[PDB]
Amino acid sequence: GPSGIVPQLQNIVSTVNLGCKLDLKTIALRARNAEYNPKRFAAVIMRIREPRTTALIFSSGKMVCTGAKSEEQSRLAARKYARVVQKLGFPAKFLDFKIQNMVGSCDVKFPIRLEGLVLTHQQFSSYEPELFPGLIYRMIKPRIVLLIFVSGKVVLTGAKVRAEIYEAFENIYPILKG
Amino acid sequence: GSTTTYSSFRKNYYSKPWSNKETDMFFLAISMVGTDFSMIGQLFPHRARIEIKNKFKREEKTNGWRIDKAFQEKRPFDFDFFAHLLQKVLAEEEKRK
Amino acid sequence: VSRSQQRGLRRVRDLCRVLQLPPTFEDTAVAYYQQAYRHSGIRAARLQKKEVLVGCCVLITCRQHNWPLTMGAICTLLYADLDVFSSTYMQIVKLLGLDVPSLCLAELVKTYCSSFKLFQASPSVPAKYVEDKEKMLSRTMQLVELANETWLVTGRHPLPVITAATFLAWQSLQPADRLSCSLARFCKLANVDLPYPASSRLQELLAVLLRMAEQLAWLRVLRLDKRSVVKHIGDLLQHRQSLVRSAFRDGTAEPALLLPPCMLKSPKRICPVPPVSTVTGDENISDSEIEQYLRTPQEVRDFQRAQ
Image (cartoon, rainbow over all chains, first blue to last red; front, side, top):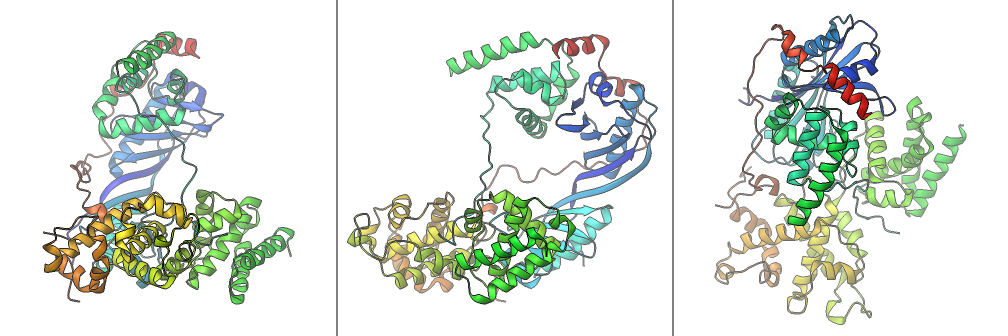
């Protein structure tokens, strides 16, 4: 039944509303871990060491948290950025936290004939070796995008919950095997 | 002309490899500035903002312990001292190499 | 009816005529451009994207008929960078929900190798370097099939594989007089640009042919190397299917292991797994934990002075 292979989560993208307008000039100047160039990009780029993540803080009070390895780590990191903003004098709240994207990876430990997969599963496969070495597999159930490499290494992305990464990998494994 | 011309990407923009002491100096910038890469990119005259950010993201992977130490080890930010020290480090080490 | 659509459809037809494509191709490519234009995101796109789109529609048409047109050929004709072409091509394939067949290797071998100027003598092509076009194409195709069977094609740009195979076919057809000529010298006289990965494909193909040579007792005894194996390529290709199967442990009936070169690179570290952590996102956040991310009044003054 199961492959015995568990995809490892490599990246989580989450969003949260701090529920108040923010002065990014103030945040940039008074935080240590902030980067702000409004002429280049309209948001503050903030980093914390644990969980090792990056946040994009917008003047609207909305925030994007990237880089966490678990949904719990993404929430703890998002709460820490919210606490940094609060200490900077803003009445920040922690509203509508939501995981938006999850990236997983694994190795099936056998080589994959991408040129063969693009023939049997043409309607889901996009294999362009003139642009990229991996086959782009757009699974419909669950709606996950997989990057399949000749080495057997697989990248899974577009998931909202952990189970969608696992479901897509369990679906692709027999297709890749035989 | 031909209909079989080789397809290669051309928008590649070159960055010089980081000298062991140019790296030591990069970690000095995380101690003085923190993680504001544009300001650090101003401390390095021949390094762009992206070059600082990619260096940070490489060091983050391979030598995580050094990124964490340079940030926890806060240091007075002296722009002038960094400029003179960087000009000398990039000169002296290049000479000894 | 749109002025930019009429201009685009005219450009689609002009590109097909310049490429000397069969008459049925123009209509299919025009239909894709019209379909593309029904999306508001394409209608409001920059004129540069509408220029690349002309190429995407013609390339998709060629791919569906196994006409071996490369993205590099289209980029040259459209004065487009490959990454500029990549974003429009990937977008329109997703947008129109199209199944795009792969580049047809057998057809690319024929078109690309016919461009090699080695079929007539000239001041730059001496008599001993002149080869029969059909003999050359047939051996190059066999070497491309070998590279494909031994995992040298998958995920790589197909053209450098054909360059390495065409060179090896050419050398093996007259080994005594052509073994001194390098890949770079060969592409220069044939008047074909040398793709950088072609040298790597060559070395991989020679390594594969050497493993095969170990499966023939009368070749195994000659202790062949990447130079001495060239005169036996004809012999090796005569029994390529059989020799590949025998030389490699990995293969089904329905020390050497047939694997892609990126699996045998053998790095000292393979996928350093993220550490297992099951920490809840509900744990207390102390004031000291947060305060380390804040600048002191002195740090604010020292930053302000530096700005």
